[PDB]
Amino acid sequence: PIVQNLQGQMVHQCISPRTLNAWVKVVEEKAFSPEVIPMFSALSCGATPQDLNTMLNTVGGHQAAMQMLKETINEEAAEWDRLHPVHIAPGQMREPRGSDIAGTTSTLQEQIGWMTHNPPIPVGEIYKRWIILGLNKIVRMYSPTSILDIRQGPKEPFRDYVDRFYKTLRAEQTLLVQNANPDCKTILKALGPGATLEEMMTACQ
Amino acid sequence: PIVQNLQGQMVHQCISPRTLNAWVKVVEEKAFSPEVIPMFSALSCGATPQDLNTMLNTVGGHQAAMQMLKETINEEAAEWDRLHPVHIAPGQMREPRGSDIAGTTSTLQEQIGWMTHNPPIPVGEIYKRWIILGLNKIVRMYSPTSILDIRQGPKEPFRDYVDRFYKTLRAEQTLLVQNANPDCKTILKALGPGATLEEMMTACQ
Amino acid sequence: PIVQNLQGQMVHQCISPRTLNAWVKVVEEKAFSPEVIPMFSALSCGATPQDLNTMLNTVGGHQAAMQMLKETINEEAAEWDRLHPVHIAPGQMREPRGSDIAGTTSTLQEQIGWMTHNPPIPVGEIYKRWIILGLNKIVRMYSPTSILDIRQGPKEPFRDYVDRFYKTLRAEQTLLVQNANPDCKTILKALGPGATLEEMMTACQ
Amino acid sequence: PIVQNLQGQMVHQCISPRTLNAWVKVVEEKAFSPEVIPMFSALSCGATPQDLNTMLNTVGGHQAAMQMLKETINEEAAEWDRLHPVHIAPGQMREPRGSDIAGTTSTLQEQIGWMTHNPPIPVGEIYKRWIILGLNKIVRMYSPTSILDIRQGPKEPFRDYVDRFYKTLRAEQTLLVQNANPDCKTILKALGPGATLEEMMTACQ
Amino acid sequence: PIVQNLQGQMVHQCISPRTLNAWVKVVEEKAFSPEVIPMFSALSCGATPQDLNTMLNTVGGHQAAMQMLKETINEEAAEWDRLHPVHIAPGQMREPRGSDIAGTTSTLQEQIGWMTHNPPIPVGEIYKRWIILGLNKIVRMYSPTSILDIRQGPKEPFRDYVDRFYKTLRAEQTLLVQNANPDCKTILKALGPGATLEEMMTACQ
Amino acid sequence: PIVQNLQGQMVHQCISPRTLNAWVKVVEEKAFSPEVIPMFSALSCGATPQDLNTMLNTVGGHQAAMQMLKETINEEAAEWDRLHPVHIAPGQMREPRGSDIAGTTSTLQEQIGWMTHNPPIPVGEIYKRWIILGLNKIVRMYSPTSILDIRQGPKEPFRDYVDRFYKTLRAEQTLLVQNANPDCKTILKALGPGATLEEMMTACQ
């Protein structure tokens, strides 16, 4: 990644073994549960495009997902090239294409040059946006259940039902009451409109 | 987070994999036992609003709780906007709204700008207060037992009973004697008023 | 905590995840065995009062002990206020009360101000003394056995007996010979006065 | 490796125990699955030739592979010498041969000298290219299955089949439809040409 | 400990959680096997007397050993006072007594003052010598077997016997041949005088 | 070890707990498999003679090997003294003997003095060479099998046989074909001379 040194200047640092392992392990343990995306974003803080590719390429499984991600990246790269056409001057900085932002046709030195320019051309952040767009699509695709099929069991505590409900809603990206069991539904109907989630959960506790 | 470098200036640093993992693991292991809150506060030392959202968003389970937390945050953000209305001057710092403090409508650069200003507009600390307010409500909601139902067993050591008693009191946020078993109750009654906890525990040991 | 940076100035640093985890884990594994106290002292090296409260508050179990600790802290804080009464001058440092030393009525900035003053008002060290006083009382209370009841078994190696003996003496805060078994007692009596522990252990080996 | 210090100058640093262990463990756990190569590249960021040899030499198993790698390295070193023949001037830098790039006939000091020269003679990066060339050949050799033999099972979810398909394609370095089961094949044929992977996976979900 | 900062000056640093845990764990796993002593010495690199006491005091078991260690320390401290008698000048450094070197009657600030003086009064190193003297005595005491009783089994590989032999010799602080089994003894006798250990082990392999 | 600080000067640093543990654990897990030697070399990067002795002395088992290593060290130290005889000038650096290089008769300060001299007298590197010489002898001695006895099983995959073959050759420090099974031998004979290992392994796959 690119970080500020103790002095203050923006310099390249090697991606750490801790970071590399953390990403690999969270994908192994969580697959594409929605919470993997904010973890990816945090683990890739200050990442160059090279670093972002390292993280994606170190994933051993889920190659259907990784291929879908490449499709999304290529679509975003194509849209970049449509909006930002490029025409080199000796010793000068060239303008980045989509494939340069994605790190496939740009060197680490070019990437550092763009990211540490004044003003910065934030190719790491632009690429991370494309990757997260693609990851969101994967999360949605691999979401196993419709919110319509999250219904409270006869003996299921309301809290556990609400956990399943909002877990599903997050993956899928009034109904809470409708999908509740008969006893809690009657209680929730009697609360009236404008009841908070806290008040509903207290009522059915 | 924002930290002091070796020189002395306040600079942004990436949230560490150690910090990220620590928070995820404590939520997995402790759920919303009261001690998770001081751990959250300590792990988010110097956190930007972006960092605070990262920590909250990396939690995979407990989505009922996370939704309740958003409600509390929105209530505090609304109360902020009521007390701090805002009317931009080229190259100047804009005043933060509630949603800017909560990191949903502000950039990392704006957040750094506010937190490192002279004097600082401590948006990280303000947001952390709102989050802890919401987390306290969750701890209280998920507290399984009333202090009224913590009573010493016939063969239960007094120490173990007192541990259950103050554990419950902490989660819920004279009675110790009343809820003691007959033998220890008689001993504690004979000590008289103004007895310390140490003296009570020695007496029933 | 407050530490020296690479330059030399005394600055605040965030309490580390390593430190936080280490303290939580040692309390989980050792409870209030006497060796937990020197570990606490070492883990809280350079700690502010805020840091000390973080460490104590992150403990999930042992709430009887934590309540007893608060009593001791309040007693020491009261004795501080008796010896150090306080009467603010704009932009100047106020004198710390007992509750300021204990971190309940003082801000982190005030704590840093006192600890980095010339000369320093070492509120972290003063509070740590009160905490260790309270922890010693807990260790003593939770010591399961009297030294009078540590007696060498008929087939117990002398070394194992001496380990139990001094383990108990440490928790409780001539008799070694008296509590030895008949065979080793006869050997130890024959050594005469002024025998070292090494010589006694060699004799009964 | 060679890294930038806090000041800014390029200096040698010892390879870390974390890095050493990470590489050894990934080879133990993944053998020559394709994802080991981007991990190698990332773990050897800024590596000298000495560091690269350390990483390769710390591998205990897979000595058939390590011997094949040496053959590839010697072929690349021979091709280097063909394109870059060398003819020493007191206190001056000599030109690197193939075996100097591979670290077998060059000292650490010579390697540092080349890599930190202005302009740099990047012997670490040149050697890493040769190693990755050799590792790719090994990955291909140890790929257990032809893509022709990756066919969807009668009850196999399409997603799991696509994972096997692209996993195999990656190791080996229209057919997706042809190798699908009868039911999904009919669905995929009906989509027509130009269907994305996302659309195919949605269709057979 | 006392270490050199990035600038070059000698400054105090907090003992790390890594160091604390490492020492506790090696004592738990190895007790007083001879190799624990070089580990202690390495883990206490640059240690103040306070740090050395922390390490010794964090040990939970082996209190017979810890009491014997105190006896040795007191003997060395007494011998120090005999050779170095002391007679304070405002703002000046006082001369260390034995108990000051052992950290029981000296403050951390005094210890830092002595260790960073020009020339340094190396109270950490002096105390570490006394501790290692005491630890050697404990290792010797807890050595379970005489070298006289290490004899090669009829079917015991010579290498395994030599491992037991020199392991025992190290703990206890011609005979190798005499204690060998009949078959290897005959082989070793035939080698003649001046045979190296390598040659003996090759001969009986 | 001796490392470059952030400024650039060569300074002594304490051997890390990570390094200490890594070495102990690799010896516990791998004994004297050939790959332990490059790990030793990497873990002892920049090591003083004191550090090298620490690493060797922290090994608890394998005392036959450690005694053989001392013999090799003493032989190299004797050969050093033969080639480098020494004749002290107040405040000046003395010339190192063999036992000074091996760290038994030299202080840490003397070792630092030699290693940071201009030009440096690299006593750490010289000693590390002697140690690795001795470790190679041990690896060879503890190699369990002759390469003559590595023959391909009737149903053994060629790859697994080649792994055993080159593993053995590495420990021991045409035949591949001769030791192959009948079916693969016929295939390898038909390839003719000058076949690469890759081509042989492809042929018998």
Image (cartoon, coloured by chain):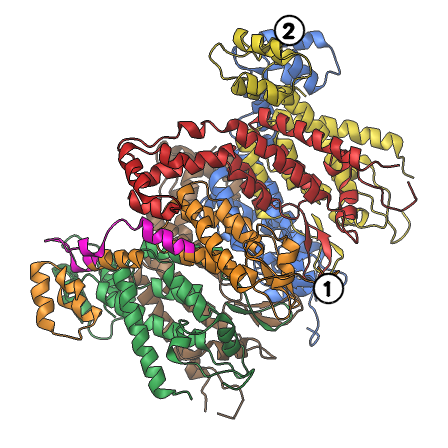
Chain colours: A yellow, B red, C orange, D blue, E green, F brown
Residue depicted at 27% across the width and 63% down the height? E65
The chain letter for the residue carrying disc 1 is D
* Label 1 element class: loop
Residue depicted at 57% across the width and 34% down the height? B136
Q: Above or below — where is C155 with respect to B126?
A: below
Q: Is residue C157 magenta?
A: yes
Residue A162: percent from left, percent from top:
57, 19
Residue count near mark 1 (Cα–Cα under 10 Å), binned few <14, some 14–19, many ≥20: few
Image-quadrant location for residue E142: bottom left
Give the spatial CA distance, label 1 vs label 2.
Answer: 62 Å
Residue A132: percent from left, percent from top:
70, 31
- First in sequence: mark 1 or mark 2? 1
Q: Is residue D113 magenta?
A: no
Q: Amino acid at mark 2?
A: Thr
Q: In the rendered image, is residue C12 in sight?
A: no
Q: Amino acid at mark 1?
A: His
The disc placed on residue D186 is 2
User: What stretch of residues is rendered in magenta?
Assistant: C134-161
Residue E205: percent from left, percent from top:
24, 57
Q: Which residue is mark 1?
A: D117
> In the image shown, does C133 or B187 lie closer to the viewer?
B187
The chain letter for the residue carrying disc 2 is D
